[PDB]
Image (cartoon, rainbow, N blue to C red; front, side):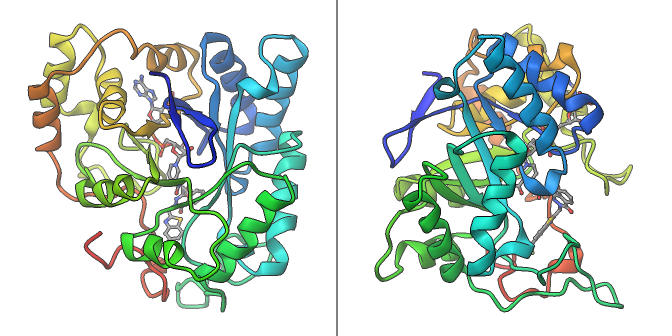
Length: 315
Ligand SMILES: NC(=O)c1ccc[n+]([C@@H]2O[C@H](COP(=O)([O-])OP(=O)(O)OC[C@H]3O[C@@H](n4cnc5c(N)ncnc54)[C@H](OP(=O)(O)O)[C@@H]3O)[C@@H](O)[C@H]2O)c1
Ligand SMILES: O=C(O)Cc1nn(Cc2nc3cc(C(F)(F)F)ccc3s2)c(=O)c2ccccc12
């Protein structure tokens, strides 16, 4: 099926469009093309500095009568510098304003780490370290809950949380809403078997980000592994007369994950959606899981001393 049931009763499309590193000069057209070829889920964030332009595209296609708001599933995330209770509603309302929406379908705590409040999204000290804020995960969760109760968002969730951090929330006395989603990096080099098992056993939906290995990530090194260029995956793709990207997108769908590949190239936006017409075999799946190397695209070294850094724990 094309959508997965969340803990709030709403249905979430399992295939969505990613928007990190989509420039404002091209993301409006990306989203318009996306909606035209069938995407209904768009993954956004204030830190991506392009929510206005995403909002332009959504607004235009509503006006064109291509889709209705109820048909769309729009996600954004609360950035690290806004974890203070008194800053959360404002941050959410900035996102809604920019996206020209009156609600979000899902709002995530982007990272478990709070950063020093201010205009700078990555506040560093003079020696390179991120400057933390004195906020904690549960106070931030409480403030996210408030957004549901005010109707600004229909569901809340988390992202880049390890299983101990998820459990902190689950075990919160007087919890109001359980997280609906944990969005994490996931691809054949970082297969996340244990955290996926944990989350699914708790009734939390997992979204896989960077499913193509984020080749456009700004800190890529020539020597890094390259998923789209892996000859082993290319051979699985050839067998199915599909591209490597289609295989990489289909792989998490068959693990009962949501997946959010990013592109601003119209041909690829279309190509990437054409993944509901074939199945990977049991052997394909096994083979792709075997490529795990615990290799993360997303893990800023300047944050490794933060008290809440998520990736010291095994999972
Ligand atoms: N929660 C978080 O912390 C977090 C972190 C990272 C990412 N995410 C979300 O997940 C999304 C996906 O991750 P990502 O942007 O890191 O990377 P990704 O989706 O793994 O890879 C995107 C890269 O692949 C290229 N690409 C797309 N389709 C292709 C195809 N069919 N053939 C060849 N190349 C193709 C894109 O190029 P073009 O765009 O130039 O076509 C871009 O360079 C993000 O955009 C964001 O929405 C969330
Ligand atoms: O955020 C995205 O969606 C993409 C993303 N990822 N990263 C790598 C990061 N690694 C982190 C690690 C922590 C940590 F929790 F681990 F401390 C906290 C925050 C971050 S940002 C970035 O540096 C970044 C910069 C601008 C826009 C998007 C991103």
